[PDB]
Image 1 (cartoon, each protein chain N blue to C red):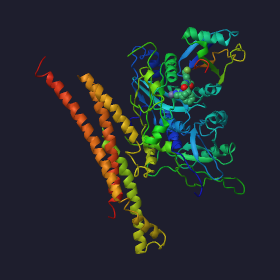
Image 2 (tube, helix red, strand yellow):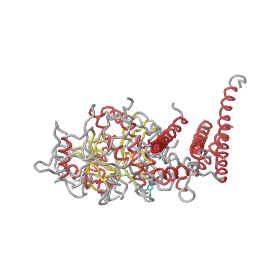
Image 3 (cartoon, rainbow over the protein chains, first blue to last red):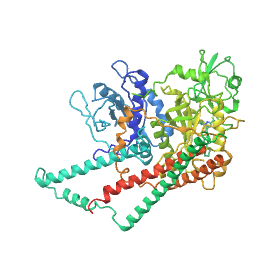
Image 4 (spheres, rainbow over the protein chains, first blue to last red):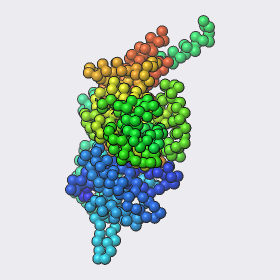
Amino acid sequence: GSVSVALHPLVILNISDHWIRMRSQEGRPVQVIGALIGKQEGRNIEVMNSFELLSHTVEEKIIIDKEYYYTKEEQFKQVFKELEFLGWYTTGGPPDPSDIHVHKQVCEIIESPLFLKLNPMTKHTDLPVSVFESVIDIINGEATMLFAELTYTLATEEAERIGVDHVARMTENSTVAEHLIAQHSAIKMLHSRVKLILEYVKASEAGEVPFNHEILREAYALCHCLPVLSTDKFKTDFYDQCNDVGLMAYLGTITKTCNTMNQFVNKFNVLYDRQ
Amino acid sequence: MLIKVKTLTGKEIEIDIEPTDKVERIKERVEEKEGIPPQQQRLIYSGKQMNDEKTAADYKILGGSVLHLVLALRGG
Amino acid sequence: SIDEIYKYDKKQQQEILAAKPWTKDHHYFKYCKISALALLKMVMHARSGGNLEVMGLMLGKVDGETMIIMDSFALPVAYEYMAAYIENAKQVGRLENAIGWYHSHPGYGCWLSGIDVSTQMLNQQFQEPFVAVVIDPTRTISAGKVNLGAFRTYPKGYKPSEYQTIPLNKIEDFGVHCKQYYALEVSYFKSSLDRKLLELLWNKYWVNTLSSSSLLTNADYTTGQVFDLSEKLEQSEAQLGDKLAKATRDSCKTTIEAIHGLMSQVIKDKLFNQINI
Ligand SMILES: CC(C)n1nc(C(F)F)cc1C(=O)Nc1ccc([C@H]2[C@@H](O)CCCc3cncn32)c(-c2ccccc2)c1
Ligand SMILES: [Zn+2]
């Protein structure tokens, strides 16, 4: 990593739920302020579970209601032993002078604060890019610090992965379609990656891009690895699995047929033989 | 004077006491309200559990303080 | 726009709480709607203890026969710490109150223990809307699917199977305390809009999906399902001579899962093995 920022998917869901709850409560969308915590290892961010930090949003000014955050500090310290304050989050578009003022207020508490600006009104494919944090630029006279965007990573643990998969579309639209849409999306993105690699190879062949001797070697290795497990033992195991699933389907088509036959005889016994 | 105790679910009960009343009297009043035994019930004010020997001298509200009722098993 | 799960209506909640419709009929609550955040935080806390046991509270409201859960907060643990942390529910700005408690069973199935059912009895007796969630971390990690444990209990002195995987030790506790609680059908709700848009981070993985290694990840789960289906069908036959419909539904779901795994394997074989032959 070049900037060592690692966001967790739980934070995004936390911010989304906060924003949706406030929007429903107050009728219209409203800007929210939060507090990202995590683990710092010198040059690592590793954001994790975030809490409310309501503070104030009065008129056009944000007041310092950080005493509530101070009370929340010892509260969250009881359930998160190895977690410390790292930054704060917001909901909106580009950074604003109000964001600068709130960041100046936050730097009073911590020396290295972040600034997440999850945008919920976005209508473009790639995800809103998390945090625009800065090293604070200083010039003669007024500080007039800005934000220098640096990249983020979506490192996630196994429990988070399972939870995210469960929330995502997985098992009116039938279960076959829901199961197949996930595979369709995964194959679609894999196909896009492979197609762009092929486009780069074609561009290098024609001469649009300079010839990099290592990218094409890696591409040749990738092409050579393409026939994955083509052994006779793999085929035997695959056919064994297919036969097992076929038997498991037969046992259950039989069950459905038995159920329908039972319904048929139940309806037949009350129509012809009235006893 | 006349305070309100709320459970976790949000159920409110309005119990009337006197300034010299003890916390055991609070628990007995809640018992007569619902039926919770005093040993299976914990009272919290301002995020701190009340001690079972102090007669509400620092809990002076004069305006119906909100108390928090937490059910707990006998002896933990 | 659907949604409408949010916007906590205070008047309706007070009306339904004062009416107390679940006092007359004991089988009032049948459906439990856990949120996305609730599940995420619950599973994260359950796995953040490993083999140790964790427990916390879960906040939500009640609508008709359904119990909706919107949030859940962990607890430090029996001492004064838990009671001090309980004040979080009324300290923050949130209108959801509290609806129940969740607690993890790391490797002991999903049932309710005797102390668990006694605490649920007490909680239901003096806090009318309450449900217990008994999720299992080890099983969801190993099998890749989340198993739910909404297990509201019966009242005292009243008289009116799914995850039976406990091999030897705790199965005895299961048998004695089995008719003292009834499971609730868990039906997950997604708020749509913001969360439906932001669920594209799942698509960012795209590798665990393309190499899922199913049909062996949860082989024990399917064997247990078939083992339960066997005496479910035997009970249906004994009654026949509608449990048969339930047995047919269970068989259909198990078979559908198996065929979905086979379809994923076939797709992977067509994608990777059938190239450059
Ligand atoms: C909701 C909380 C505050 N609560 N309310 C009331 C009620 F009395 F009001 C009562 C309670 C409450 O903490 N119960 C409880 C009971 C038993 C256990 C352990 C106990 O058996 C020990 C064996 C393991 C176990 C498996 N299943 C329940 N346990 C726990 C518990 C679960 C996980 C972590 C820590 C504690 C909590
Ligand atoms: Zn338990």
